[PDB]
Picture 1 (cartoon, rainbow over the protein chains, first blue to last red):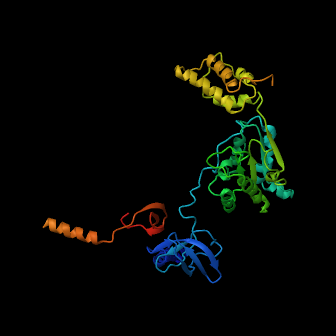
Picture 2: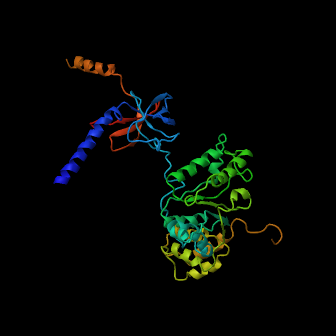
Picture 3: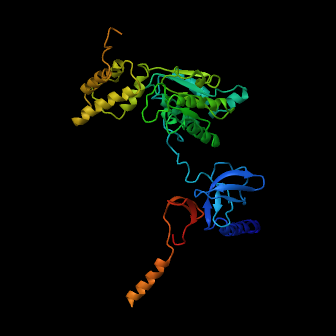
Length: 362
Length: 51
């Protein structure tokens, strides 16, 4: 009664009076611009997309700590005054492309790497989710891990399941998008990726399939020989040009890290080397059982037979035989897939592309 | 009488300066909308009371 009349009543009345004063500031004569520089005199020069020049003062609700060069502030049409700081107009429009919040992945499909899975967890999942581990002991957690191995081992799926446990934004980078040839432009795009990761501080940085130009391998976007120097050394200048104790963790992954520049490896940031291998026959039943959980199997079909037949195959090859055997019975409109479809699937998918060494016995 | 009144009512509409063209970008709770004009730049304007 007494407190509610002296608090709630003047609060709702003051908020309505502040909006009335915005008619001379945020009212219809309103425009925007691009901030250039700020001076200690409470004045700045801002250029709108129509390329004018406006030198005015700074209004309320905003300080100079939030005003940075290159951003977009808010202007006025008549008085031309700077209102306040705002985010990127229309936004960069980067929401989910290489980045997301909580991807859906488990440890069953990546099974078989458990020997090397405990290495990435303790160096990434443990320090990020449990920061008290390295703080109480005073040790420095690994600031990055390198990924090397044959494809099909779930290289992307390895860090995908870790991102769901950390409950943080998981960044990715395509190797071919940084080397795009417009004019130069190679190092310019690299800075914009790490700049966004510094504002919100997701504390997760990952790169999938590092390629650049080893030799050629491109047509539309080439870059020449000068692109190799300005690209591969730009990723080095991120860790070498800045010292970040506990936040940015850079993780690099590709098919072959040997041909890469030893300077690009940046020793001392990545203290862990993880090797990828194909899963053994013991872990194939976990992946096969998931895809066949919704599949109708006949009485003569045994799961232990398909696992024994598989020799030197990736994780995608387990679901490939289930897809091929499922389409054979789908064309004939059968409920339970016959054992003949499973036999023809495991034999065909085994040898398709390269049947023979083409020369000698090797 | 209806033809002359119609032509007279349409006369003040042509004498009106008219309006620009733009596209809505984003909206807020302040009733201020960002409209991107093709020839001009982006302008944050207040919505009408009818909408």
